[PDB]
Amino acid sequence: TRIDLGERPVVQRREPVSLEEWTKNIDSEGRILNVDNMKQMIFRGGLSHALRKQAWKFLLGYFPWDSTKEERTELQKQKTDEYFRMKLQWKSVSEEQEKRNSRLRDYRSLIEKDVNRTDRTNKFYEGQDNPGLILLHDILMTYCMYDFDLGYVQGMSDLLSPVLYVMENEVDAFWCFASYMDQMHQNFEEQMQGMKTQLIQLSTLLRLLDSGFCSYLESQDSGYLYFCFRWLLIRFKREFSFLDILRLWEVMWTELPCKNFHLLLCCAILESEKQQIMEKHYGFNEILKHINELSMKIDVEDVLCKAEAISLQMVKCKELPQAVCEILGLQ
Image (cartoon, rainbow, N blue to C red; front, top):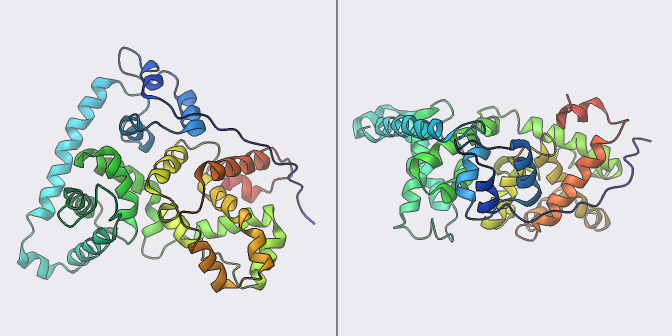
């Protein structure tokens, strides 16, 4: 016996924010007028392709919302200088230095490995002669100079590639990736807490939604949800088309409707596959295969709707447990 969530609302989404709608909210000083409203619009509709390059800078934290234009143009000047200063640090490393730096050449081999593996049918990264791959490589090496303790960990190029695609500039892509890595950091740490914390948080959400399904997974030894690992590490990057991911991440970065919205996206997908898994009586292996084969077969708009529908239903609940309250950011 547990919580009655009540009925699930139906969610309606809106058209993406146009370049024109954006420019209207900018004053003469280049400040943004209604932030909360713009965030609501970006969450509700996403961003038009033309608006994507400027607005992501604000979404990712590269440009502060309260900034003016002169503060931004001043910021880019410092960030350009700060970037190439760090790029020079690894680029001036000699063969002799590499022999004696084990951590550095380890990072480099991991980078070269993932880069060749990243988005190779995309126009930006296609072909072995593509400048885009060099940019991927360079930005990732420079991030090793920026954060040497973390360096490069597998899956970080999957996070960078859409950011590099949108920004197209080496300096801009780095600092956007840099702020993106700040929130994504504990995913790639040595003993990784925050992958474990997210899996714990995720199961907590599911036990509230359908506890029968959770009891099922425990019987199938799927109780710790390792099949959700790929989802959480790279934020669904492998489950969606490149264009779909752009829209998916735009919406997430608004930080609306609640905290850890990406966990509810997991719930959204998981409730759609809930019946097939239980009927066909899938075990841990069949579940992992079923979810991996679910790639590219998921509609973004449908999932964003269900995920928000769920959050609305949880926040409204007076009997909602405190553990979930913390996860959704109500505390």
